[PDB]
Each structure stands twice: as C-alpha cells, then as structure tokens.
Length: 543
Ligand SMILES: [Cl-]
Ligand SMILES: [Cl-]
Image (cartoon, rainbow, N blue to C red; front, side, top):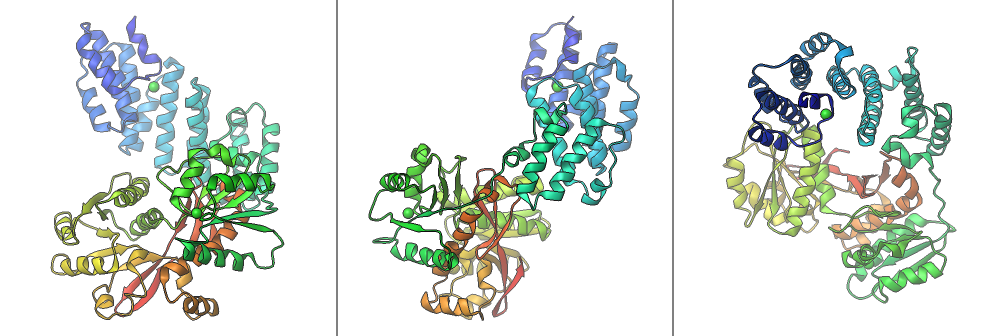
C-alpha cells in the first residue's frame, strides 16, 4: 500500500515528486505524489503553487483527505489566516496522525503562534513537535527554532513565567532566564549553562544544545600575555603600518603586555609565524595586506593554537578556529547601508556598484543583509560611467525608493547632477569613499552633494577635540590615514576582548571605527555612523 508514504517524512524535492506523476499510472498514487509535492512546495516557499496543486486533487481516500487537511492548515498559517488555521487543525482527530504528521501538525501550530507574536505558546507547540521528530537534523532545527523564539520574547514576561506543570517548558524557561540574567557576565553565564545541563539531564536541549549556546558553555576569559604585531613598516605601505601602529600604541597606553613587532615588508609571513611560535607568542594582530592574509588562509594550520586578529578580509576569508577578520572593508559600509535604508523606510533600494570585482563583492554584501531584513533581493546594477545610473533610477523609481552608490567624490557629484532633473527628491546613500577633506573644501561639491547622507567612522563627530586636532594636523588632513589610526586603536580594544567577541553572540563594542560586532565567520561587522550633507555642513544623523 503506497498511500502509507504520506505518514512518513518527505525528504525529496518538489521537482522529484511532480516528475513521478507521469511515471505513475495508478490514479490513487498520483494523488499521493501531488500531496507529497504540495507539502514540500511550502518548505520551498511556493505556497500559491502548493495551494494550486491541491485544487487539482480529485477523488481522495480517507488517508489522503487527512494529509490534505494538514497542508490546508499549513497554507493558511503561511497566508496569515490564523483563525482559519486553528479551526482547521482542531477538526482533525489528533490520534489518527503519525509521528511525522503530528510534527507537521504542531509546526503549523507553532507558525500560527509566531504569527500572533505569542512566543511562549510557540515554544509549547515545538515541545510537542520535538517529541514526534526522529531525524537528528530535524531535532536540531527545532531546538534552535525554540531558542530563537525564547530569545525574542519579552524579558519581563520570561522572568514572570510559570512552567505550567510542563517539565520541558521549565527547563527552557530556566535556560532563557539564565541567558537574559547573565549574558553581560559571560563568565557567570558559562557556569550557569554547565549547571543547567546537570539540572535537566533528560531535557531535549541537554542532548542537543542550541548552536548559539555551544560557544558559551565552555567560555574562557581573555588574558593576553604578549602580542605579535604584523604590519608593513617599510617600503610600500609603510605609511599604512606606521599609522596603524600609532593608534595601537596610544590605545596600548601604560599596558605591561610586551608587543613584539614584526615588519612584514622585511620578512615573509611564513617565517614570522615561525618566529612568533618559537617565541612563545600565542596572540597576533595582523597582517594587513590581503596578500599576506592569504598566506595564513593558504595553510591555516600555521596559526594552530594562536589567536589572530587579522587587519583585513579577503574573498578567501572563511571560518578558521581562532581567526578573526577586522578590516575597513567597503562590504561592511554596504551592510550598514542596508540597515540604515531599511530603518528609514526604504523598500525599493537601488544599488549602483562599479563594474569590477570589488563592485560585485560589495553589492553581494548589501544584497545578503537586505535579504535578511526584507526577504528579497535588492536591485543591484553595475555601471561603466556615472551617467548609466540616470537610466537605472528613472526606470525603477517605485515607492519608498532610495539609491546606494559606491564611487569617488567627483563621480557622485556627477550622479546627483544627472539625477536632479530625473528624480529631484531622490534619497541618496553613499559610503565613506564619498567624504574626503580634499573635496569637502568646495562649495560646488558640497552644494551638488547637499541632501546626500553617507557612512563614516564615529571618530569624525567631534572635530573640536584635542585628539582630533592633534591627529588631524599630524596626518596632513588626509581622512584615509585618520581611519587607519582609529583602526589601530580599535585593534587593541578587539584583541583584549577576542574571546568575548568570538564566543559571545551579539557582543558589541564601542570603538573609534564604529560599533564592532562579529558574524558567524568572526568577520568584524561595523555599525557605521551616518552623516548627511545639509547645505554647507556635515551633520551626524544616526549612531
Ligand atoms: Cl515532511
Ligand atoms: Cl601586512
């Protein structure tokens, strides 16, 4: 009896099941394949295709009518028909479903709760779901889902929440309360989590701990004994390594930590790591040059047992144990733009990138962050000449439209000039590449850039400070160099909070280059400060 395949999980693709329709000549099995395909189309976020395929279902037998209802209730939950979904589930004899069918029952039930912003209930549904799951990966996904729901719940409600006689809910409430009570004390949280596992040894999360909490269970406080500083301090890039070094030492202050400096322009990164290793050094800052960083990435076993805060990030950057990437990368300024534009209400962002490798990498960075906030791709378009943007804008000027463009100051001046008569009220966003002292001394540039807002480091907020004037004068007024000094200062901040940054999720630091945080690849993200050209001045707006 092939109809029983609806009681087991459907692990194949929708394309697989549809393609079995032609190969099946028994009408009863075709309806089964349509049901199997229709319920995976939802997992593939094709609800309207799933519903359309259910309307094609003709004569069904009671076993098929049952699985049809589960999908009908899952579709309603996806269409935010919460009242309908509930009344459709309750109409099913819950004792007639299989464990796989019960997991879909409660998953729909959890989706309804989440739609209504009822986190506690959503957790209670996934507790029932978990009891009916068998695949380890399905367990893990449910565990992490449950932890996401608990983490998004109101902290005040959690502290005042009863287990309701449900042991599994108890174990969860204890876990999330410990996290909320001790995340700012990561050493104490670790001690709580280890104790949680011994308080609820038979709890589901005790066997499969949430992935966010795996790095915290065995957390360790950062304790830097000595540093190796890898920078280009001679030849090409000397000004870059010297300026970065200047910030690092000023942030260093009266620290007793010995810092052994290595000049990467006088030695190979291969031998530096060797010297550092024999030297007992277990903590490196740098290198800076992308080519030097790729040496480590060409054989990550070189930094075995070391904590490395690279001062750059390359396309080959990835997740390596005890490696973090802190660069002034235009990819981060593009991600901060996706956050800024989203908060400002933009929903049709137009991204103009240069037609080069950098433009594709920065444009992808924006798209990724926009997919998270909006669940859709951004309209990226590369340009040969700044004029090409004028055609790009006038053809996609939907509602709540805004432009993002990475380009030199002189190039942006052209873009906003050609876009004046085309979209006079256009909202324009740019990166730090738009702001330079060699161009902020103008009246035409600042007048033909009025209204434009751009990201840059927070250090430029206070231009009347002693440090700014002392640094601004010594650097010759070159913005790019000041950004390197700041970077060197923040590298000291980062290296001493390396473990927190690497193992504490959401950990944020207030540095001179922005709000520093790490993603899953310990790629140091920067929440940029946003300034806006208002007539003749530069006014901070956000962060
Ligand atoms: Cl399934
Ligand atoms: Cl370097």
